[PDB]
Image (cartoon, rainbow over all chains, first blue to last red; front, side):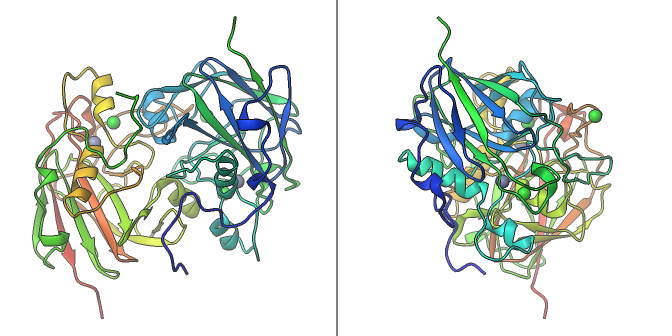
Length: 231
Length: 231
Ligand SMILES: [Cl-]
Ligand SMILES: [Cl-]
Ligand SMILES: [Cl-]
Ligand SMILES: [Zn+2]
Ligand SMILES: [Zn+2]
């Protein structure tokens, strides 16, 4: 039961994502690797023309992925706009990904995996875990988004649908959906080029009551590397 | 242009939706038939337990449909939460439709059509029409949402994905999406029961450059009728 209005920016609990940043201002160094720990989220600032590599180190982990325009969290990578622009349910290498203004925000340059991702499913939240029978607080992607932005002094005005990297949620004839383990492999990566200055947020999904992060249900970390704009 | 922040509440143009309401406060007289004009949007207040018929009078018209919690436009019927809750891409009669808090907001009670509706595609907007080659302002569902809420003194803080009633844009073999004419017929209706006090918004989609409102590409009106809460 709810006794207050919904607050997009307010976390329902805490983990180290509230206080720990990857680097000052989210500005990752060239030639460095960084890690989003298991069950946590982090924000990353990109300049136009830079490219971000996201690496599924252990091979079965989902990365809930968002991007916001620098200086405006009201404009963001938008799944419901991405789909009509591409005339496709999920992106492939070469696809330009748009914001809620239908302008380019990112390009998916590379994907070493079989290409299975999800754009249909909301980020997990305390309500999802309560409905799955969990008692007490559970780490969750929506809180990780809120905290990761907060750690850079930013405030979302809405929770967009994530791009669920490596998530395998097939829709079959009839419209039904299934929660299945991923088909990615150890070390698979995706590479995104920024088409605008952006703030990217990645949450290492902590879902451990369904097999979506692997049959073992043991959430793991993700590694990232930021490439500078080409010479 | 896009050197201003995106504003969820700000219409990009005007039509009579800015001004004209169905009834005072959007509070419909029970059992009276009202009409949302072609190309326009209107807001409708419903008390918990009341039900709303939406009638595709001419049979090929799409209705972009939203619902917000009364007193809190930050909580809304949410496509990306609807789908994991139902384990289905779109709803069918009997399905309880959830908000972005994963609690019931509406129940879909009846659908006389074959049950084809879209939950995947953003509401049309000025950017969509520009990209389809249109010159100047085109009526659009996003502006209709903004105006319809504004006409009641309300302001949205985000533009949720609509529930596109009667829209036939299936995901086909291999992941592509197709834009097809509706499979609804003259007089088809849906019936929703409010599970909370809500503000419903319906836009009669003005899309006339694709056959989604029928092969003739001639946008039409939609009728609505409220029934009172039961004993
Ligand atoms: Cl989930
Ligand atoms: Cl459209
Ligand atoms: Cl397939
Ligand atoms: Zn998650
Ligand atoms: Zn429309």
